[PDB]
Length: 14
Image (tube, helix red, strand yellow):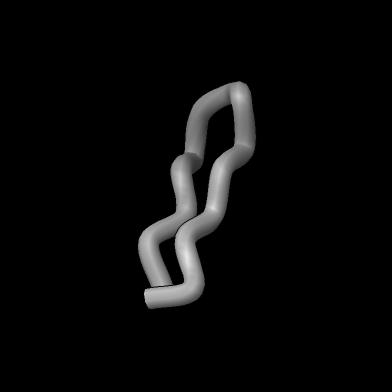
């Protein structure tokens, strides 16, 4: 579920 608001926009399946 963890998604970054800043670049690089990286998301983790959690």
